[PDB]
Length: 50
Length: 245
Image (tube, rainbow over all chains, first blue to last red):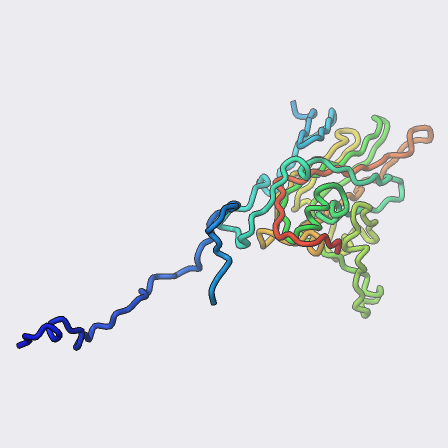
């Protein structure tokens, strides 16, 4: 049995794979939604960090 | 109740006292492009009154020795008004039409004109006459504009197809002893929801005398035919510089 705290609070033997993503159904191409004009600050979706 | 009509669209108005009726083409009125039929994602501009209005092209003379004339749509409005600027400034185009043809004569005049709408009126040629040359029509015959073009062999419509079966498309008659106007309402007809107005013409408009004009010496010998047409439910998409052809 495990007594010391570094062994009880250990992530050794975690066999479960931790995935960030999940596969969702995409039977069709994504639909386009209606958009209007945007004239604000802060929200700038064209600028990226590649 | 049926011989009188007023057609109002935009800043324009036509009266007629000697009409037959209005032909609504293939039982479909013009409409706008649905989101299911659409594929392009840009927002189209829908200018209601500046392009959907009656435009008057020119005036052909019905003589004794006439053979017929054709006009190609939308080529007739690609240099005219606000329609022919939105169509040049954009890449895509969708519209119906209301065509309205005018020919006035007296009660002592006789004659008949077949006024018909032929979709995808592809223009063939005499092939050298012998059929050996694979000749082709020039640009000033397939897209002749508002001036229209005079049929060489109207029996085959310059396409090898008989005039006699042309009532299977839209049509009216202008029988001078019955009517002087011919009104056809055409929807957008294409395999695609939009298309180019400068490259592709959706349909043609034939005006052919089946029965020849006759009058006795003393009557007005100048019997003009005037084409007057209105876009309907117009739509333009894909904006860039203005190109004419």
